[PDB]
Image: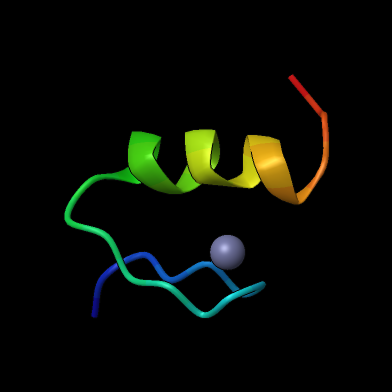
Length: 29
Ligand SMILES: [Zn+2]
């Protein structure tokens, strides 16, 4: 019911967190 990093399947209260979180998963900005 809340964004979830399909990568580490991490859920956050904010989207930015996810996005920014991904930054690590890769390097796409
Ligand atoms: Zn993740």
